[PDB]
Image: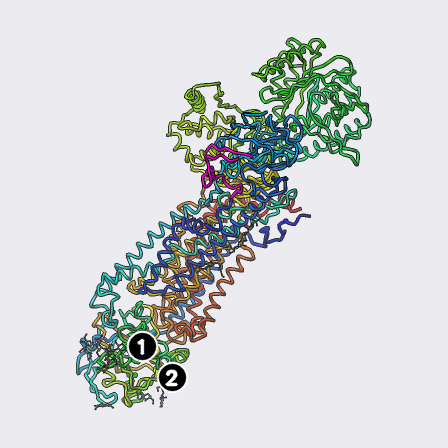
């Protein structure tokens, strides 16, 4: 009896069930037809979507640079980017006045003096809820190799890790006390150091002469502004408030240190900190600041008070704010629609050319022993 | 190193610690590539022949410096150690299979003795030089042994040399004169004598030595080959041959023509090595771009990096650019892919497995499939031409039948050949049914001839289906029909075929006793075996001469004398006194040797008809023989015998005097008839050769056998033909010719032959012959023996010789030496830029096999001296078509497509990373969450491409045998060019551009595209956004490029994509990651995610889909059209016929 007989399976003998993917022009015409159909459909859909949302972006670096001090001068047109369908209403965007003012404010004890800008921007139509409010930072690179690994995780989680492990961690230059003493910084990275410092004071809707009272504060919240998982990442600190200090740049805010009146901010609630410490990808990123889910902003000449605390033209950067309204797709991005339409259009024109060159023009009947290249 | 041997006191001139000089190798034989004690360094140096491993080892020792990105212990050092270890494990397992069959051979038993006082059974390895040895019938010989005695007196043993030299006949060997008398097994311990020998020489038929047999004082008996039993020779017609082992180990001429299984490499590895170097070049170029741009951007006091990041990785922009350079070299490591070599090892091993488990190449009589022995080279078999072939072992089974005869001008063949069947069915005539009806006529004639024989005297020794000379006309002519004189003619002829022989007859009792015929060559064995199947069966020489049982009645012949066969005589004779009183001399031999010894001026029509019939028979591939007779006289016989025994008594120059006296009696003769014996080919060998020659392969039969048998086999196999000029390059080793005249004669022959081919070997008509792949002029053959071959392979004639051998359609070397086999293979292999297969069955064949690119052994049961050193081990020649035509073009196309798609894959990955670096001031920041990069090339994408390489097939297992011309595309090496590589890399770069800049656009050119509105523009969420569509794109491109979408391939594609989704969704549900804490619920549930997931794979696979469909329609392939044909039908006949 023969024992070395190789098993006559249908896999060992390479006989598995299969489909010989011959590209006869009854198979590729249908492929290109279905691709063109699906992609032109999705392109029309996404174009309608990216046209159903509407927004307004205003840049405000010349506030500290060149805004006037007592009169509401107009903003040049290279700052207003307003996508609003219902054009030529009683209000029209691209006409916003703006004025800066050095103001003596209080924080905990010492009443420091910051510098403010005030922007009167008019939206011409209502925008239904979930009106978000992002800030925009050009030429800011959060995506560097040393920058993106520079923080302690357990510390943000809420912990008193050590004075040694924090001292030699990947957050090298900013992990110990800048002054003489040997305290340890609470957020020990330079990713938490450079957090955006401007402060947006919610749109005070000027009197539209319907409710003629001067103030109509469209109260937008800054809570529930990040993913709940982030809240599961952070936590109030276990440090004794004795050995922690703002790293170098919260000084103009914690001008005396972490104390019983200026306490170390709990991170599970500080949601703007949670938005910042998730590192953006490009240098021209947006980030979420406020929102409102339960009431529609009406057409009106709103006014926002932007404490311009972040000196950004120092590195030729730019900063701005946007008030986009959302849809199921996202915010206004005209490019998905155009990309889908372009792919569908080229698939359609190649379908047309293939059906032509394989049905109407010469069809090159299948398998003839004339092209075999050993019959010539 | 000329050695000496002593048998019972050593020579005091080699004292203690001075006697071990003349260190003789151990009788073991190592064909394994690695020893246990030295496997590691050898295998490491072999794996590092791949240049990329140098780059990977340098990059591993470079991450130890704790300044760049990835820490050293696991991430970057586990892959190298694991890859090296699994590669070494595969190679060690393969080498151990070779080693286990090696150690199976090394334990073969031999009766050893010089210390044992008896010839106890031992193994081959236990054979020290100078130890007595006994050998029995058909025993493979352990080592080169000098004879000392044998079973029969006079010292005659027979050696079947077919394993070393392709000669079939049992060559006679003589025991040395003094010392033959040691019949016992223990009377050797008083045999005191000394042996003198010479250094080991690889020339087979040149050896000399001496013996000192110590009242005897001093003896001396030179020992040529006639005392030398070689190692592959099989001892026959002798019960015991009490020899002495003189050579052992690698001193033997059988082993002295090989290395130690020189490790072959797959010829795709080298072009792949150049491609690796080019990819490393582009890697360095892009890393230098990165370093310069990073330094330029980091040496500014105006960028936002100076303010917010207090930093520099060195107190200079130049130093930080340098650090970034090396760190980028770490990040862009996959330009020279690490996963290339392990993927290719895994693919090649699986293809070797699939070769091993194919029943379509399972030979039953030996019970083993096409077991591969080098799993690296499975793709080279898709490129080879120049299938060099042995003759005696591979092509011919070496069973010799008796087909036809021509007696009294009358032919009796009634035979048909598969050779002729193919030769006719190739043209329009006799296509299919004629074969069946003709074989039916042959069966009918066979049964009618057996019936006619039964009507004659009862023949118990005759056995149906034990006879090949079927001729009913012969039976009726011997019965008496058609003539009373023709009966006498055929009767006397069949009596002559039972008189001229020397065969020994033995009766096998039981069922009607079939008699066995032990002869000196299977030629006369077939002669006599047919001379009993038509009456006139033979018995033993019962103290007189032969006894013939003619038509049921016995006849005792006294044999007067016999003149034995020789290589120079070409004929053999015997004088016998027949019962009719008169004595008669028979002389049978070659056709052209008897036509010279014939009484002239007689039987003009008879002799011319016999000449034309032998011409027909020798053209049909049969090995003809002529028999002649002469009525000798009593006084003439006794006087010739007195001259004969007088010449025998003259001890000096005796053989020449015997040949001179024996040529005075064989001059006047007359032609009884002419036989036609056929040396049987294997099954399907003519069809195999036809199929291969249609593919594009050129087949050079180069045997070690005589010059005319080679031409016979060239006629059988249909290599030769009847419309073919013959080029016989010969420099007759004219006695004592000046050597330079040898070369001058050879040069003139080469020059006139090249002339007539209308050219010469001017070295300009070689660079135009390094780029030509065309079946040559089909009307030329080149027959050249070893001597002419030896002299045309020396300095410059070689080149000329090459050109000659390139024009002639066929080549038939003859009496060629193992070293010369290897030299011809190496001349065609190096002188041209071409691949080369060598199929063999023996020692000469092992030399030919290790020197060729692909070595195939045949398991011809002759001792696997050429199977333990081959790439593959086939059982028959007919499976070579299956192997080369199915598992060759398949494997080659598969490896080409695998490595092309693989370069594409790694290109798209690393160039997407590079574009991201472009968007972050070239400071090398991963966008892929430090685990996508870890698991990408491992899990998400490796299985689709390895499956495309292992289990993809273009046409079929049978449509490839039905259309061999497709193999031409592998001959000219058109599936792995250097434009498929560059086109695939350009494709990868384009697809990286698209598959990075589409999701980047989607989720970065807008404020937080996330539907409910939250941060998904993060550095890692964008990583998922471009890393899921990238995996789907790569697997689609690996799928679009395959031809046979089957169960496993589509299953693996689906599981790889579903596995990236599952791995994300599972790994981002815990706090352990903290960058991906919940990435699944807030990336999946978006709509831009699915929009990009469906748009980037199409936008990446659309250009090659368009190119593929158009380049199928407007321009075809050959495989394209054969698949468009075999799709509908046109090959269902072969499929249905083969499956059942
Ligand atoms: C629109 C097309 C613009 C670019 C035209 C390139 C023309 C290439 C011509 C050429 O030499 O093709 C060579 C190959 C295409 O051969 P194939 O039969 O499909 O290979 C399948 C394989 N034998 C298999 O079946 O397994 O070529 C390839 O395999 C890949 C190259 C095709 C183009 C790659 C994309 C570049 C696009 C850049 C602009 C967009
Ligand atoms: C044998 C396994 C060896 C694994 C070693 C290994 O690290 O995988 C390697 C290949 O390894 C393979 O491709 C083996 C694939 C075999 C099939 C596995 C499929 C599982 C499903 C993959 O290594 P890599 O992903 O190319 O490493 C890149 C790291 N870098 C990007 C930082 C330079
Ligand atoms: C580590 C595993 C090594 C397996 C070694 C092995 O036996 O491979 C085998 C299976 O091979 C396979 O089924 C695939 C194994 C994975 C790829 C090979 C290992 C990576 C290199 C290859 O089988 P084979 O060599 O084709 O069979 C030889 C037949 N013989 C046993 C008579 C010689
Ligand atoms: C909001 O954030 C921005 C950016 O983080 C922040 O602007 C920063 O203020 C810090 C100081 O609080 C600046 O750092 C200084 O830079 C100057 C110039 O290089 C240095 O001379 C300063 O060193 C002196 O002062 C230190 C502090 O007393 C001493 O320790 C030191 O010995 C020196 O005497 C100091 O390093 C930083 O440059 C700016 N950033 C930019 C971009 O200009 C802003 O103040 C923040 N506002 C609030 C309210 O948090
Ligand atoms: C983390 O690394 C820093 C840098 O090496 C370590 O530095 C220094 O730590 C000592 C020990 O507390 C500090 O000294 C205290 O300094 C005051 C001077 O104001 C001195 O009067 C006290 O007697 C005491 O020595 C020192 O100021 C501090 N210097 C700096 C620049 O940080 C630090 O100790 C490391 N952390 C730990 C936990 O070890
Ligand atoms: C969105 O803004 C509107 C602005 O009116 C908020 O409505 C006011 O909410 C406050 C409490 O936060 C009430 O005291 C006022 O009486 C409300 N005014 C009106 C006219 O309704 C609304 O609460 C905000 N909602 C969200 C989700 O932020
Ligand atoms: C605020 O409190 C801190 C400590 O409690 C004190 O040192 C500081 O002087 C206070 N502010 C003012 C303006 O005095
Ligand atoms: C918005 O509502 C909060 C909660 O009552 C309140 O503290 C805040 O002053 C309001 N905003 C304005 C501009 O009044
Ligand atoms: F012994 Be062979 F036919 F080279
Ligand atoms: Mg052989």
Q: Are marks 1 and 2 in contact (CB under 8 Å)?
A: no
Question: Where's residue B986, x and y in %?
Answer: 38, 52
Of the pair B1110 and B244, the residue shown nearer to us: B244
Q: Chain of mark 2?
A: A
Determine whether the beta carbon of the residue marked 2 sits less than 8 angstroms from the nearest atom of ligand 6: yes
**Distance from the alpha carbon under mark 1 to that under mark 2:** 50 Å
Question: Considering only vertical position in the picture, is B371 above or below A264?
Answer: above
Residue A28 seen: no
Q: Chain of mark 1?
A: A
Question: Considering only vertical position in the picture, is B417 above or below B1102?
Answer: above
Please give the residue where the numbered disc 1 appears in the rendered image: A164
N-terminal of the pair, mark 1 or mark 2, is: 1
Determine whether the beta carbon of the residue marked 1 sits less than 8 angstroms from the nearest atom of ligand 5: yes
User: What kind of element bears circle 2?
Assistant: loop
| Farthest-out residue, front | B215
Question: What residue span does the magenta drawing correspond to?
Answer: B1-30
Residue A295 circle label:
2
The residue lying at 20 percent from left, 85 percent from top is: A113
Question: Where's residue B1050, x and y in %?
Answer: 53, 58
Could you tell me which quadrant the N terminus of chain B lies in? top left
Question: Where's residue B834, x and y in %?
Answer: 45, 38
């Amino acid at each position: 009896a023969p024992k070395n007989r190789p098993p006559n399976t249908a896999f060992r003998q390479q006989r598995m069930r299969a489909w010989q993917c011959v590209l006869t022009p009854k198979l590729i015409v249908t492929v290109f037809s279905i691709l063109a159909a699906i992609y032109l459909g999705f392109g029309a859909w996404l174009t309608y979507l990216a046209h159903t949302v509407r927004d307004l972006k205003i840049d405000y670096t010349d506030c500290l640079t060149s805004a006037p001090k007592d009169d509401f001068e107009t903003i040049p047109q290279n700052h207003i980017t307003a996508h609003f369908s219902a054009k030529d209403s009683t209000f029209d965007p691209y006409k916003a006045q703006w004025k800066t003012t050095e103001r003596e404010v209080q924080v905990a004890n010492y009443t420091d003096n910051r510098q403010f800008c005030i922007v009167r921007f008019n939206i011409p139509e209502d925008l239904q809820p979930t009106i978000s409010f992002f800030y925009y930072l050009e030429n800011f690179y959060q995506n560097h190799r040393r920058y993106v690994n520079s923080f302690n995780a357990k510390q943000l989680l809420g912990d008193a890790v050590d004075g040694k492990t924090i001292n030699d961690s990947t957050c090298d230059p900013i992990t110990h006390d800048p002054k003489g003493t040997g305290k340890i910084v609470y957020p020990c990275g330079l990713v938490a150091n450079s957090i955006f410092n401007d402060t947006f004071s919610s749109p005070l809707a000027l009197a539209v002469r319907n409710s003629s009272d001067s103030s109509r504060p469209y109260n937008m919240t800054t809570k529930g502004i990040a993913w709940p998982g982030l809240k599961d990442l952070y936590g109030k600190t276990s440090y004794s408030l004795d050995q922690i200090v703002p790293p170098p740049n919260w000084e103009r805010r914690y001008k005396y240190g972490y104390q019983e009146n200026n306490p170390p901010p709990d991170l599970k609630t500080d949601e703007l900190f949670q938005n910042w410490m998730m590192l953006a990808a490009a240098p021209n990123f947006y980030k979420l600041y406020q929102k409102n889910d339960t009431h529609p902003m009406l057409a009106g000449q709103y006014e926002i008070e932007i404490e311009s605390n972040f000196d950004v033209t120092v590195y030729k950067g730019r900063k701005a704010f946007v008030i986009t309204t959302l849809s199921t797709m996202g915010s206004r991005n005209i490019w998905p629609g155009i990309i889908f339409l372009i792919v569908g259009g080229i698939c359609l024109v190649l379908d047309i050319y293939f059906i032509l060159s394989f049905f109407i023009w010469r069809p090159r009947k299948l398998g003839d022993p004339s092209y075999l290249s050993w019959n010539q | 190193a000329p050695r000496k041997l002593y048998f019972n006191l050593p020579p005091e001139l080699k004292d203690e610690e001075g006697h071990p000089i003349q260190q003789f190798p151990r009788n073991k034989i190592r064909t394994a590539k690695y020893t246990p004690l030295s496997f590691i360094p050898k295998n490491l140096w072999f794996q590092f022949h791949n240049i990329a491993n140098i780059f990977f080892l340098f990059l591993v020792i470079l991450v130890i410096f704790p300044i760049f990105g990835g820490v050293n212990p696991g991430l970057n050092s586990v892959p190298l150690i694991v890859i090296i270890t699994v590669t070494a494990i595969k190679d060690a397992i393969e080498d151990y299979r070779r080693t286990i069959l090696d150690i199976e051979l090394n334990n073969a038993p031999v009766h050893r003795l010089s210390g044992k006082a008896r010839f106890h059974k031992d193994a081959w390895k236990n054979l020290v030089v100078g130890d007595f040895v006994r050998i029995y019938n058909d025993d493979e010989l352990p080592a080169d042994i000098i004879i000392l005695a044998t079973s029969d007196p006079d010292g005659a043993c027979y050696v079947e040399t077919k394993n070393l030299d392709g000669e079939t006949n049992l060559k006679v060997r003589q025991a040395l004169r003094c010392g033959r008398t040691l019949k016992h097994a223990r009377d050797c311990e008083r045999a005191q004598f000394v042996i003198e020998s010479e250094p080991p020489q690889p020339n087979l038929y040149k050896y000399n030595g001496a013996i000192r047999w110590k009242e005897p004082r001093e003896m001396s008996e030179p020992i040529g080959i006639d005392n030398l039993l070689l190692r592959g020779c099989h001892l026959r017609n002798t019960e015991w041959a009490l020899g002495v082992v003189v050579f052992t180990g690698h001193d033997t001429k059988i082993m002295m023509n090989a290395g130690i299984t020189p490790s072959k490499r797959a010829r795709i590895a080298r072009e792949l090595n150049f491609n690796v170097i080019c990819n490393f070049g582009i890697l360095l170029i892009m890393c230098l771009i990165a370093a310069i741009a990073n330094g330029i951007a980091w040496g500014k006091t105006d960028a936002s990096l100076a303010w917010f990041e207090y930093g520099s990785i060195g107190g200079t922009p130049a130093l930080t650019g340098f650090i970034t350079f090396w760190a980028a070299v770490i990040v862009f490591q996959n330009l020279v892919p690490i996963s290339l070599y392990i993927s290719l090892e895994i693919v090649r091993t699986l293809q070797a497995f699939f070769i091993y488990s194919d029943v379509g190449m399972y030979y039953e009589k030996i019970d083993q499939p096409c077991i591969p022995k080098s799993w690296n080279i499975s793709d080279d078999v898709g490129q080879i031409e120049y299938i060099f072939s042995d003759k005696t072992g591979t092509l011919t089974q070496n069973v010799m039948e008796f087909k036809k005869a021509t007696i009294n001008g009358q032919p009796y063949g009634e035979a048909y050949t598969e050779a002729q069947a193919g030769m006719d069915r190739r043209r329009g005539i006799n296509v299919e049914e004629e074969a069946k009806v003709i074989r039916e006529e042959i069966a009918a004639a066979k049964v009618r001839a057996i019936r006619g024989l039964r009507e004659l005297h009862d023949n118990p020794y005759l056995h149906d289906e034990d006879m090949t000379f079927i001729a009913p006309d012969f039976v009726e002519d011997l019965a008496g029909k058609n003539g009373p004189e023709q009966q006498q003619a055929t009767e006397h002829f069949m009596l002559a075929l039972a008189l001229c022989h020397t065969v020994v007859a033995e009766k096998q009792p039981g069922d009607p006793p079939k008699m066995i015929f032990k002869a000196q060559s299977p030629d006369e064995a077939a002669l006599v075996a047919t001379a009993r199947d038509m009456g006139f069966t033979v018995l033993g020489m019962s103290d007189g001469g032969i006894n013939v049982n003619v038509m049921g009645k016995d006849m005792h012949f006294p044999v007067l004398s016999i003149i034995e066969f020789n290589s120079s005589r070409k004929r053999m004779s015997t004088i016998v006194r027949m019962p009719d009183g008169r004595i008669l001399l028979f002389c049978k031999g070659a056709d052209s040797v008897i036509y010279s010894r014939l009484k002239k001026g007689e039987q003009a029509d008879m002799r011319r008809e016999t000449a034309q019939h032998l011409e027909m028979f020798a053209v049909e591939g049969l090995r003809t023989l002529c028999i002649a007779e002469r009525e000798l006289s009593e006084e003439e016989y006794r006087e010739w015998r007195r001259e004969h025994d007088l010449a025998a008594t003259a001890l000096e120059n005796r053989e020449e005097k015997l040949e001179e006296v024996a040529d005075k009696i064989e001059r006047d003769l007359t032609l009884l008839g002419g036989t036609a014996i056929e040396d049987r080919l294997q099954d399907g060998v003519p069809d195999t050769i036809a199929l291969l020659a249609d593919a594009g392969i050129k087949l050079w039969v180069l045997t070690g056998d005589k010059v005319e048998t080679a031409i016979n086999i060239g006629f059988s196999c249909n290599l030769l033909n009847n419309d073919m000029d013959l080029l016989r390059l010969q420099v007759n080793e004219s006695d004592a010719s000046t050597e330079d005249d040898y070369l001058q004669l050879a040069e003139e022959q080469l020059k006139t032959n090249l002339e007539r081919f209308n050219m010469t070997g001017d070295d300009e008509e070689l660079k135009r012959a390094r780029k030509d792949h065309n079946a040559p002029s089909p009307t030329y053959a080149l027959v050249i023996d070893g001597f002419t071959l030896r002299w045309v392979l020396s300095d410059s004639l070689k080149q000329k010789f090459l050109l000659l051998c390139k024009q002639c359609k066929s080549v038939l070397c003859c009496r060629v030496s193992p070293a010369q086999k290897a030299a011809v293979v190496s001349m065609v292999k190096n002188g041209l830029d071409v691949m080369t297969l060598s199929i063999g069955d023996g020692a000469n064949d092992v030399a030919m096999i290790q020197e060729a690119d692909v070595g195939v052994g045949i398991a011809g049961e002759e001792g696997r001296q050429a199977v333990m050193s081959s790439d593959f081990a086939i059982g028959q020649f007919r499976f070579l078509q299956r192997l080369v035509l199915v598992h060759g073009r398949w494997s080659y196309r598969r490896l080409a497509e695998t490595i092309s798609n693989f370069f594409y894959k790694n290109m798209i990955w690393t160039w997407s990373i590079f574009w991201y670096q472009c968007y972050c001031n070239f400071d090398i920041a991963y966008i892929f969450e430090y685990t996508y990069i870890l698991m990408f090339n491992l899990f998400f994408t490796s299985v689709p491409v390895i499956l495309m390489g292992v289990l993809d097939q273009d046409v079929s297992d049978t449509v490839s045998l039905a259309v061999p011309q497709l193999y031409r595309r592998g001959i000219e090496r058109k599936e792995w060019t250097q434009t498929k590589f560059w086109l695939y890399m350009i494709d990868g770069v384009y697809q990286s551009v698209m598959s990075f800049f589409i999701p980047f656009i989607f989720v970065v050119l807008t404020p937080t595209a996330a539907g409910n509105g939250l941060d998904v523009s993060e550095r890692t969420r964008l990583g998922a956004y471009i890393a899921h569509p990238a995996v789907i794109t790569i697997n689609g491109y690996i799928l679009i490029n395959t031809y046979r979408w089957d169960w496993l391939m589509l299953l693996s594609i689906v599981l790889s994509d579903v596995f990236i989704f599952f791995w994300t969704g599972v790994y981002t549900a815990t706090t352990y990651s903290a960058g991906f804490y919940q990435a699944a619920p807030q990336v999946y549930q978006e709509l831009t995610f699915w929009m990009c997931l469906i748009v980037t794979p199409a936008l990446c696979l659309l250009p090659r889909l368009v190119v593929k469909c158009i380049q199928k329609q407007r321009f075809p392939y050959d495989v394209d059209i054969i698949r468009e044909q075999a799709n509908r039908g046109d090959f269902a006949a072969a499929d249905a016929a083969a499956v059942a």
